[PDB]
Image 1 (tube, rainbow, N blue to C red):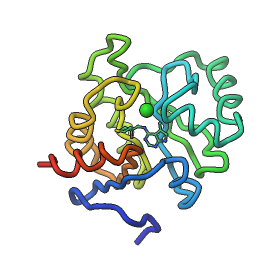
Image 2: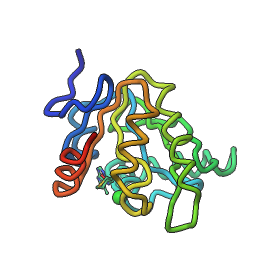
Image 3: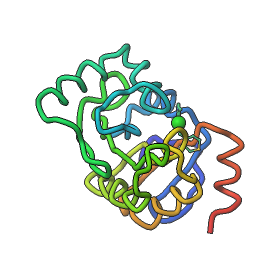
Image 4: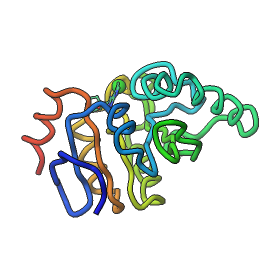
Length: 167
Ligand SMILES: Cc1c[nH]c2ncnc(NCC3(O)CCSCC3)c12
Ligand SMILES: [Cl-]
């Protein structure tokens, strides 16, 4: 039993809700919140910009130190940093950005990072401003993630389409 509430159950391990991931994290304080990161951990917009804003820019300050030490992430890769006031940890995961020409096949590699964590609150990787088809992202999620994932979909119209079209 966990404290996630109001989710529709898609499979044994994948759950979904129309919710603002920022407000969800603040309520649940999950062990892991996933950020839709880029390789530079520049949290300017989309999910990343919203999560960072909710931390009063502390996420960005921490991220800049991470990059200065370690260099950029790989597309498909991740790192674990603090969850600040939102979660114990933030798993920064880089899905391919179609608006940069990145290979959509890397979306599966991106979701594989979730399997290192027993339970996660997450957005759909590569959705929104990363330009991929969210229906495809949900399919890859269900077919790749084996741990317990609670997906927050900000857009109500999109949430309804994802549910109604789910096979
Ligand atoms: C931008 C943003 C702020 N807070 C959020 N919580 C969750 N998801 C988000 N954007 C990604 C999205 O859910 C992918 C699937 S379709 C709708 C968009 C956001
Ligand atoms: Cl977005």
